[PDB]
Image (cartoon, coloured by chain):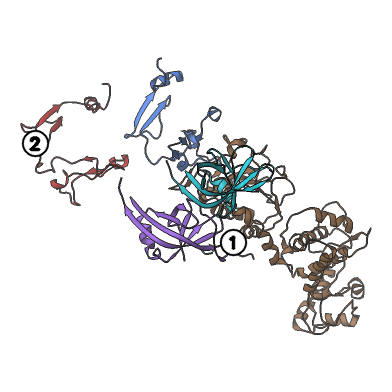
Chain colours: A red, B blue, C brown, D purple, E cyan
Amino acid sequence: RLYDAGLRCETGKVGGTDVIIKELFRRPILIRNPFRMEFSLRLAKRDEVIGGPQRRPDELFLINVADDEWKHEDVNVHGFKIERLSDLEYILQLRSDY
Amino acid sequence: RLYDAGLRCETGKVGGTDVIIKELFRRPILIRNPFRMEFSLRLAKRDEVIGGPQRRPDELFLINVADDEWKHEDVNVHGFKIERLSDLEYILQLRSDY
Amino acid sequence: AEYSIKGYLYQFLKYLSEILAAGDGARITIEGAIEDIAAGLTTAVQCKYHEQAEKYTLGKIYKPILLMLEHFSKNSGVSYRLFCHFPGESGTKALTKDDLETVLSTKGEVLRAIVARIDTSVDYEAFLDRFAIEFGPSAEDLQVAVLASLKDKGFDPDDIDAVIFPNAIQRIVDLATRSDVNDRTVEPKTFLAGLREVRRVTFTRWTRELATKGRMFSSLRKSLRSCLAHNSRWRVFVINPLTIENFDDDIVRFIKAFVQRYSSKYLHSNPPLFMLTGDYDLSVLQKRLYDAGLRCETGKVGGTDVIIKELFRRPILIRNPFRMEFSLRLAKRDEVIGGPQRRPDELFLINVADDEWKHEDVNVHGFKIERLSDLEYILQLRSDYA
Amino acid sequence: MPDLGTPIGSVTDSSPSLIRIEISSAEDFEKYKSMLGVGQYLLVASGNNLYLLASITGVRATHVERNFRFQIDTQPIGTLSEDGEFSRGSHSLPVPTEYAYVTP
Amino acid sequence: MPDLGTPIGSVTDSSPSLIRIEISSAEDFEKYKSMLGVGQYLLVASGNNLYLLASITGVRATHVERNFRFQIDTQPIGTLSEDGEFSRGSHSLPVPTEYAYVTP
């Protein structure tokens, strides 16, 4: 669906179902003029990703989940509870008014 | 009336009564300096238009219509109900006050 | 059938030699050939032609007589004639009854086959009184004699071969065959002035089969070269499609050729215009040209009636990558009213008598065609003809 | 007379004694590199139904970013009409935006 | 003396031994290309009721996008008045913004 919409995703899979971590957190190719992005977003299931990142994440947004293995004292761990997705669209400044 | 006003339109008709999908959803020639545009607007009658487009629209506006085929779960639909067109000009930022 | 036109060609050419060699205040008229309601009671004649022998022997020429006798058989009022050239013969020679019967005779197996087709009860002596035979000289020398005579008359030497003579014989061929109310006789005094005043060229079935065929095309082709060299200039066409053969199919070919040679460049600012006179439906041609690859400029904002300012505008052109807003202009003559602000540099009238856009400071070239290929050749689109 | 193919490039500057042609695509140049050496001949358009023959005197190739540039310098020798006639000595002048072709 | 016609262009740079002229449109140049080759002649206005006859020594054509520019270089040969008198030797200098015509 995201392909039909006009976007491209990176899943970390070299053919096989297994997820190679070193190929999901890589840096993309970026030409300035004319602009182009190799990929725009990453997408994966949690149960599949077995490991961690070499460099820790700045912010971690947990929506409707209790605990994860990537929590640590040196990360800004935000936690919410919402029932519709427009709520987040308001928090993150995508929608002007509640 | 639009020509008398100073505008050119794309209808998709090539001589005959039949409507073609390709010619309507066509990119126009744009020259920067000096500024000139092959056309500014696109006009059609729904029933004569059969088929679908290549890229599903980014926004669809329904003004006193209940249902339309192009309604989909990846299109930002907006349904209203109006009495006079001056209302919509307010909604679309054309006039300053009700 | 055989429809051996060389006979009728000889006949109309000999009539032409008569007319050019005629006394003042004399009316000469001709009888229209059969092959065209059978107008005229005794104004119909059929002929053949054959000139390959060293000496005059009636035996060898069996073939014409069979069909001519059958032709007399088929219907009654209507004359019959013939022309042939062998060395040593002049004038008219009347065969006898036994001699014609010998032609009737099954001298060969083909003739025994053919005789059965002709009816048993048929006139022979009355037939001979009704049919005569005429001799002729070599045809090419005759065609040369016509042109030499016209030179003797006094005309510009170059203009004769190209324009004067084919248009002149065209009138003979029109008179010989027509379905209208008018006279059938030609007086030289009124005949000559008409041809001297009017300038146009004609390509048609009979004109093709002449001595000066090759000399006709090139002389015209060479005139239009100076015009077609230019990148930017206004050109206008007017076609009348009744007479032309296979118009619906060939017109697309012609347009694609003309555009690909003369409207597919960034320095080609003003595209051409085509105007068709008749009861034609344009939508079909427009759609077919769309499928071909081209795009047209109709002139209509609302598909009711034409606006002149929109039809004569200038298109947007982008250099690299190259595109054209439109590559041609199409319309119907009747609908158009008024004239452009700027006069046409050229106007091509095809199968048309007069138009209201004519003027003194505008060139006008005229044609009369039965196949469009001859125009493709005239405008350098194709290398050879027929 | 035959079909002459698809243009290699376009005129940028002209003169009675020099024509300069520019190619901007590497693929085309590599496609016809064999036929674009010094001494070889090119056909340039000067109006409808007329071509001019020119001789290559120089080739320059530069890649600069601010993509590809290929310059060809030519010196006319004569003209060649469509019907297939050749004549030495051309006082004509091609206008920019015209097309260049390789001689079959 | 007679009607000369619509002009081709205007003067840009002048001097005692050189005059430069500029055409800006391709239609006009394509129209009078025959009359603008080396060795032919042009008439340049220098005041009311006076003209200068100049011989072409060069043509140059270029296309640039900030459009066409055509440049003609000329050398002065003499003076021709309104009445018809022709005199070799030229003392006058043509000021810019002055028209040039092709010789009938």
C257 lies above or below B91: below
**Residue visible at 47% across and 50% down?**
D97
Q: Is residue C315 visible?
A: no
Relative depth, front residue between C218 and C229: C229
Q: Is residue C297 above or below residue D4?
A: above
Q: Nearer the viewer, residue C224 or A22?
A: C224
Q: Residue at x 13, y 28 (%)?
A: A78
Q: Is residue C242 left or right of residue C149?
A: left
Measured Cα–Cα span from mark 2 to mark 1: 78 Å
Residue underneath mark 2: A70
Specify the subunit that label 1 lies on: C
| Badge 1: residue crowd in 10 Å (few <14, some 14–19, many ≥20) | few
**Mark 2 residue crowding within 10 angstroms, few (<14) / some (14–19) / many (20+):** some
Nearest the eye: C126 or B10: B10
Which quarter of the figure has residue C168? bottom right
Q: As displayed, is residue A96 above or below residue A30?
A: above
Question: Could you tell whether C372 is left or right of A34 in the image?
Answer: right
Whole-percent x, y for residue C199 in the image: 76, 54
Which amino acid type is shown beneath numbered disc 2? Trp
The residue that mark 1 highlights is C382
- Secondary element under disc 1, as helix, strand or loop, is loop
